[PDB]
Length: 219
Image (cartoon, rainbow, N blue to C red; front, side):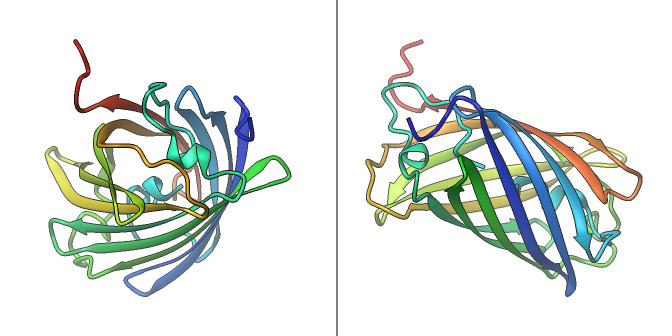
């Protein structure tokens, strides 16, 4: 019941990428049981960003994943206390993004606090040269480990002039209170930039995420 069928969120990110510091604030909304959400993000410090928006976009909401009835929605069940998540992204050219995130519920809205560290992107690479064009649809493979929910992704960023720039991603999602963990399953995710201004100081995103059985789908 805590998770309403229409939910808003507020997000704050403090970050560095290759030592360039910045802050982002944003608001979002969606339908947690339908797996759909939008967000409006604004660069509040360190803009215009001297790197690709796309490395930040996946850091702005796993309460909004559509789950089959027989897969426990661990992250929805974590509320009202909520959950933390930690992420590592290894990009194929040696760029690294590490993220920590706190997700809570205050005034009937989700509150997201994000800390991001991006390092070792090549000065001539597509991230620092802003040559990326959004993520391909992803499958996150989910499994329980060490009393937390883990997910692994082979994520693909489209490039200007064609082809892709890959990232291996691993995330740990941990409820602040003990709730029922699921077995192994997959989450199909598509994240779109729906609008941006010229220098990506103002960006709107849309994400659809649907959990699917990895065993006994029953086709």
